[PDB]
Image (cartoon, rainbow, N blue to C red; front, top):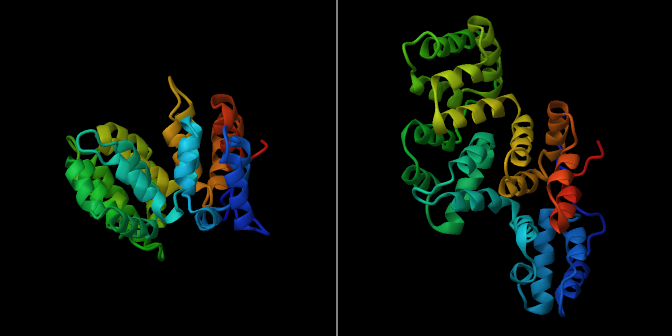
Length: 318
């Protein structure tokens, strides 16, 4: 499976015409929500920015501000998300997560655990350019403890490259982890942090397997037994991301629509953020792991223009 998103550039794109469509959908009393979502869900993010620019050049009005005025609810939240340039969306989500003692650790974890060193470097740059603070400084100010240190490790965007798998190191790391958790009276967190936070992805997939054999336990189980709270949640998100970013995000989506209340914010972020990267791959995980379409579950748990847009974004029959 090469990585595939569910949204692509529209062939025969006319941004000027698309701009004309959105203006008509909003000029006058009432709003044509349907024309808006059909158009936007079927343009790529880059194309959405071009449309936004044509709208302002034709009309001297701000497309995004107009849609915020005209729209409401979850649907408006999802259009606003869709409109955020791809290069800026993770930094936007991270900035809104960063709120002193009210910080949303869950967002921090999800994005920082699942993004590549390359994505992370681009995010730190965008964040700085847009907000005039340093992403790493704000995270440190808004978090503490081992959780904080793991986030900082990951924020270095410095994980070992997927080079030839030093097979001797594999067993060593696997034993180190065994001695730091199950064998220890307590836990050596720093050890988990360095190995899980810094070794290559392909190396760690080998370490994980070797860990089951030498220990009887999957590394995820040892994490749940040796750690707690935000650290635990982080280490699990990193291990799941090492195993498969798509599988990790399939599950995130799963648990967004399961449980007492729907996590619309998580729903929106994962569909939008991954729409042009690996959302198909995620679709295929969610299927194989949860016994339903991403589609079906979005369909059953959401309603409205919001629903119609998600489903247009998600894609996927069965």
